Each structure stands twice: as structure tokens, then as C-alpha cells.
Amino acid sequence: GGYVNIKTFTHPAGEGKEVKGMEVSVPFEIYSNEHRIADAHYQTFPSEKAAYTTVVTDAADWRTKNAAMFTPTPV
Image (cartoon, rainbow, N blue to C red; front, side, top):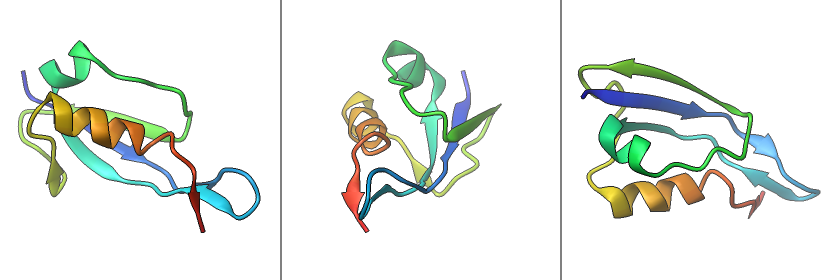
């Protein structure tokens, strides 16, 4: 039950490239069903209510947001 409140941190990822940080609240069951942790640049805290403005709605939404944590983008 409740939410996993994930904040990831903006950081360089190759010259001219970066990964932007995000703050997302994910229902714990969606999170525990499938997550990928490949970056150390994040923190998590749990809560009964979503602490962040961006709230994951379903598994597909989370898959998308989780992937945006590992995809380098041009600065």
C-alpha cells in the first residue's frame, strides 16, 4: 500500500549529454512488480499519500518514467 516517492538527480552522462532529474510518486505495487535501478542518483521515501505532483497511474506509465531515468539526453 501507499506510494514510493522517488527523486532522481540531474547529472552528466557523457560529454554534451545528461539525465534530467525527476520527482515521481509510484503506487508501491506498481513499483514492486517491476522496477529497474541502474543509477545511484536517486533517493526514495514511502508515504500513504503521493508527495509529488507527478503521480504514476499504471504499469505502462511507470515503465516509461523509469526508462527516462536511464536514457541520456543532449544538454
